[PDB]
Length: 71
Ligand SMILES: [Cl-]
Image 1 (cartoon, helix red, strand yellow):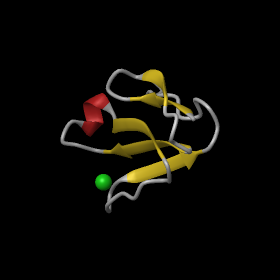
Image 2: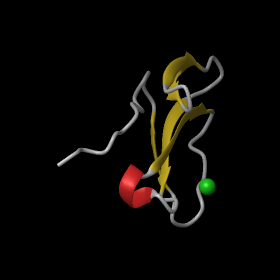
Image 3: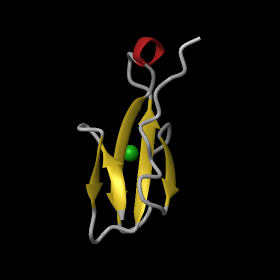
Image 4: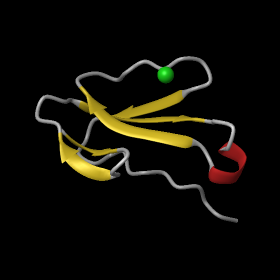
């Protein structure tokens, strides 16, 4: 599967991966710089601790980097 990967934010081939993932959470700068985003690929949808969100998908490049919409 092909997925976007942080910190390059480029699409990479994960020949042995099955899903892409988007992990987001707030650090101390979340108000001014938005959530931190970790994009990657995995054989299965990884697990995240409390306060961290993860959305997994199973098609090439289905985890585009989500920027914050600027009002
Ligand atoms: Cl985590």
